[PDB]
Amino acid sequence: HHKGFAMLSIGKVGWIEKEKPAPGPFDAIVRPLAVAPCTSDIHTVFEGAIGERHNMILGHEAVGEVVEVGSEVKDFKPGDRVVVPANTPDWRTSEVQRGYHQHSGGMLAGWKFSNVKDGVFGEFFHVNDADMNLAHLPKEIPLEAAVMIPDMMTTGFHGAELADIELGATVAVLGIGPVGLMAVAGAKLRGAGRIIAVGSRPVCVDAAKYYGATDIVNYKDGPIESQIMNLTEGKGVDAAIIAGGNADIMATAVKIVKPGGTIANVNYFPRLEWGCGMAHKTIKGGLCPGGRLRMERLIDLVFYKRVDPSKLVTHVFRGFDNIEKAFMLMKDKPKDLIKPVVIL
Amino acid sequence: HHKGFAMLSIGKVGWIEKEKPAPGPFDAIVRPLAVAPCTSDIHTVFEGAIGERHNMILGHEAVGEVVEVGSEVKDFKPGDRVVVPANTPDWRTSEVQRGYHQHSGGMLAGWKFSNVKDGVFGEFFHVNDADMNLAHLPKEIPLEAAVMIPDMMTTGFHGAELADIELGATVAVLGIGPVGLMAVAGAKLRGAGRIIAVGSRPVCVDAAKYYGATDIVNYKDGPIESQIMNLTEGKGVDAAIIAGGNADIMATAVKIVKPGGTIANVNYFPRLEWGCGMAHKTIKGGLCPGGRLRMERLIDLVFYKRVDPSKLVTHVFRGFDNIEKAFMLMKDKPKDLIKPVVIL
Amino acid sequence: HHKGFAMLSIGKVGWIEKEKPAPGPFDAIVRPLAVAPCTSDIHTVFEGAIGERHNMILGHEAVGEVVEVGSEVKDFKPGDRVVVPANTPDWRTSEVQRGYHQHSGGMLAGWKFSNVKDGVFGEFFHVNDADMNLAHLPKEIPLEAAVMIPDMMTTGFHGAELADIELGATVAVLGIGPVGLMAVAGAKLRGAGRIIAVGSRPVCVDAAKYYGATDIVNYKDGPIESQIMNLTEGKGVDAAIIAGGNADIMATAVKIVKPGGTIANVNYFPRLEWGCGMAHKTIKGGLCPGGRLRMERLIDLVFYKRVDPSKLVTHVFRGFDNIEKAFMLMKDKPKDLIKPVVIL
Amino acid sequence: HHKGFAMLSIGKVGWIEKEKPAPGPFDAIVRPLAVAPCTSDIHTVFEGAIGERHNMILGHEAVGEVVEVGSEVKDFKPGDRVVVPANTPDWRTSEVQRGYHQHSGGMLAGWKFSNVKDGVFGEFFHVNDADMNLAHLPKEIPLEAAVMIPDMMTTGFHGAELADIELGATVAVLGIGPVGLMAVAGAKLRGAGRIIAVGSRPVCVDAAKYYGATDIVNYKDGPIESQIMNLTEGKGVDAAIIAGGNADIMATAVKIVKPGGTIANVNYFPRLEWGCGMAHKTIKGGLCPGGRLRMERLIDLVFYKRVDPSKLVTHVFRGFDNIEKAFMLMKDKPKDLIKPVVIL
Ligand SMILES: [Mg+2]
Ligand SMILES: [Mg+2]
Ligand SMILES: [Mg+2]
Ligand SMILES: [Mg+2]
Ligand SMILES: [Mg+2]
Ligand SMILES: [Mg+2]
Ligand SMILES: [Mg+2]
Ligand SMILES: [Mg+2]
Ligand SMILES: [Zn+2]
Ligand SMILES: [Zn+2]
Ligand SMILES: [Zn+2]
Ligand SMILES: [Zn+2]
């Protein structure tokens, strides 16, 4: 019996008592050391993104310490400091063998935390297939930087990877939230040249400039498409990454990308003509990549100072009782907030 | 001064007389030996697909004999039997260096015939960059089979190529017109296993069965999506090729393709969720591939009996005066018609 | 306690008694219905390819029926007719997540049969990770055709896949043994145009002509390189697949492939210059692909009549006692032998 | 009639006077503003790398100003400051349509400077297909940095591109010459994690540390293979780039790369086993990339401060007469020399 911050119903949250999870032969029990609320939790609680839930613990971004393992777990033991990916696929299924985007398949059943399984906002949580999902966290990486790996960094970096960025190419990132900031960082990591970031919030604009954006487009000089086309002298961009917005941002991305380019869509929750190139494009989407290898490679990127995700963390809280406060801060989204982190 | 079948205005066609085209240093003049009307010509004439045109010769699918060449033309001489691609890109521009889909770039200005330039339905027509566009036609290939190469075969085969077909994968082809039939043939050429063809016309169904379709889905038996999902026992298809229909066929293709799959759109003229794989897809579109290398490789495929496009030709006409009759047949689309060919 | 045909010390084979294998929670026990000796077994026994072995049952190409399964096996039950791949990777390790060639990784520890584990030439054998390795065999596929799938078909088809074959490209297959014949079939399945097969044995030449080879090069007519260059008028081939021979055939393959082409090496057991394209090549090698998905896709290819591997089977034997006779036939390769099959 | 620094014969070098080149309709005449000798010139002169030459002007790395153009040249006019790529392919032949490595084909005939055509070490030189080869140089890029683009930067960056580097992967660079330093920079630009540089010269080691190398392996501390395997704890590297050395470095690269990895060979001038992964590798080689688009993308990388190639320049000379001194310095290869540059 442990504590957990759970969704009572659509629009209701509170602290409840639940039975302490037990690990199977291939599972592990992890207690969190640092957690971070996400906009997905808010969409679930208040927008009914995944339907109706009752007494479901929220949260899917945690860095924790292993406290219990199954009998068949070999690579991790209690006391090990680990990074828990947000997506934890089932690896004992032939579906994982299918594979796409140069990674493993079956990445639809991996979205378990806070969807069909208790989240990380508790004293303990359950990780399936621990040897296939968990990754060791070196002691030289701070907790606030490490907690950005499980969801934000992996989603943004996969958005950059799917954009088919060539060396020196011009890349546009629509939406400069945390996922968009990580998309800018990933575009820089892919050898992009000019990077155009679309956004208006001063703190997000400063973060985008820090992470490698060379041009900032504000939705006050005029339409986004006109500004971007004027920036590139009518040539457009080689690739665009969609990280936030509404359906109009998809039309804008189609408008601004050159024929043969790629539009990557990682934002969670027309006709072919001879004289118009708007339909001569590739649109790739997916919240695919999770697992131990992905986490290990991101950890290697952080460890060797290729990227510093600490700039995403604008608010730091101490103690278990501040999870609700961080969630509320995520709800009302003040102007100076990018991503809050609770250190346990 | 020569004759040609031209679009008088939106909805008006007739035989007009025009000045004989002259070739530049890198150009060639070709007289046609076999031509084929397309649905694109009908869309331009009667649906205003490309705007208003005046006395513009129609047609973009011809097999012809070189009549005269420019001073800088080296690989072709008058008397050579050649295949003229529908797309003839400008090759003396840096745009062709920015390629995609493992071919050259600049494949938007290549759509010249019957769009911004006189078509092939005349006694002569003009081909730009002859050494980079024309391809030699061996005498062992019949004219009716060869005339299917310039547009239908290349479009269908590129649709199959962009679908990312793996060996033994299940492929669905939506629309079994000539482009869809060539898409079925290309899917077979890419090592597909089960091929599901969606269509109802008996002649097109017979052609699809001939070209490698193992299952036929008729829309007179219920929704396409439900039938296809029943055929695959709820697994869906690995890839889908869109060759005809309306915007609802795009939704059907998105519904039937498994997560991580590819939807290829060669038919000329959702939100990311944890529990729904509809948005976890790749959509590739383009009427890209033209030029001499593409024509030569298709000619090699025909020559070595890898594919026989003669089944597409259901009506054969002799004489220049039958071009109007073939165009009218294309307009009224009778029961037994797939593709008419006029032999000069 | 069951019977098995085993290698005794070296150059010595015989029938021995061994303890009947028992399955783990994720394993299954399979009895064979059809088996096929391989040249790899002969290299192991007589050439010391893998070192010294004692009482090790040989054979790695079997089609069998499930006899019993572990408690955690869900997709297969006793009585099911299955195809057993030659490569059976360990799937409960993070190594398979790495991945290459658009398939799963860790395909080095999968070579277990007759290498570090008892082979299939016994009354029973052990298959690890049954739900991830075994594949259902439909009743409409004959045993002789099905037993070509586990090693020959997968190796040849992966050789064709790694060759980066484009539609209509010219492909050369060096060595027309069973793996080379399957490479010819795979090249045809990938949309190749001209296919040049290099070999001299009349039965293998006939099989190569059946599987899609358009040109046959005999080494009794001069050097292979000179003949191939004469066939292509000095242009060379777009890709080459090496299926048999020594380092000299690798040198020939480097010589005959055009700059930028790919040489695929699936045969088990230069300096960069401005004016010479010999080193401007890509050489891909690997006995990679194994597992349930690979077997299922190959089974789909056979089921839908995309390929008929029955032409490989030249000798058919009945009864358990004929395994030694088939192995001896494999040893002293006669004129009319391609692949012997023993039906149980 | 102009002066030029030419190779008199094998081992003989001096200043000669030659007729001033004249441009064709698609050509341009360029006078150099900064030039850099290369090891390729020394191999040509003192080692007979390309055979015997008589009065052939050397040099293939220049940044210059357009002096005059042909009648068909449109994108460049006299007075324009341009970057001249070392490889200048013929763009009016169908061969460029073939294409590989996601760029254009026909790149073997692009190696013209100081091979089959007068080099850049003269008062003027000839550039074929100016609109397809030349690239505008912004005034904000210094000459010393810009002159590293034509050969060193493009070769190293293509070596990094062909290595198939994934985010966070470990990359080894064998050879820490200027091409190897640019390979380290390109590996960093591709999102590599740990980068291991193999070299011993202190100036080259310092440059490698500057460009992103995290580990340095000195051959005075034991075998390279053993040191690298100890660094990675026996796992090896995900990819290796060969930029200098002898045939033993290829064996070392094969030994250190993990199965399924890629070895890229850009340094100008095993059998498949079940238990050994040495042959389960991909070897890619080529001095491929040249042309206007490549130069423009590299210029964009330099302009937006993604890479600073000024660290390569250790010796700067002023005046035309110092070309011989720079060439001699390249011959003697002193301790503190990486790349000399002559500013005109
Ligand atoms: Mg993905
Ligand atoms: Mg992973
Ligand atoms: Mg295309
Ligand atoms: Mg072409
Ligand atoms: Mg493989
Ligand atoms: Mg598999
Ligand atoms: Mg290349
Ligand atoms: Mg270029
Ligand atoms: Zn999240
Ligand atoms: Zn058409
Ligand atoms: Zn075998
Ligand atoms: Zn050089």
Image: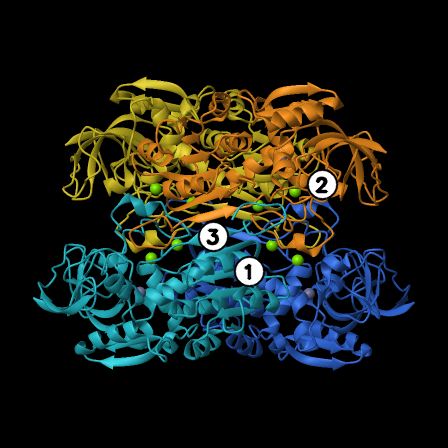
Chain colours: A blue, B yellow, C orange, D cyan
Across and down, in percent, residue C286 comes to: 56, 45
Q: Residue at x 61, y 27 (%)?
A: C330
Q: Compared with residue C232, is residue D153 higher up or lower down, i.e. above or below? A: below
- Closer to the camera in the image, D182 or B296: D182
Q: Residue at x 30, y 26 (%)?
A: B138
Q: Residue at x 53, y 71 (%)?
A: A199
Of tags 3 and 1, which is closer to the observer?
Answer: 1
Q: Compared with residue D108, is residue D206 higher up or lower down, i.e. above or below? A: below
The answer to whether mark 2 and mark 1 are in CB contact below 8 A is no
Residue type indicated by callout 2: Asn
**Letter of the chain that mark 2 sits on in the rendering:** C
Give SS at disc 1: helix
Left/right of residue C319 with respect to residue A275 in the rendered view: right
Q: Compared with residue B250, is residue C2 higher up or lower down, i.e. above or below? A: above
Across and down, in percent, residue B149 comes to: 37, 31
**Letter of the chain that mark 3 sits on in the rendering:** D
Q: Which mark is residue D283?
A: 3
Location of mark 1 (residue): D256
Where residue D180 sits, quadrant-wise, is: bottom left
Left/right of residue D256 with respect to residue B105 in the rendered view: right
Measure the C-alpha gap from mark 3 to mark 1: 13 Å
Q: Quadrant of ligand 4?
A: top left
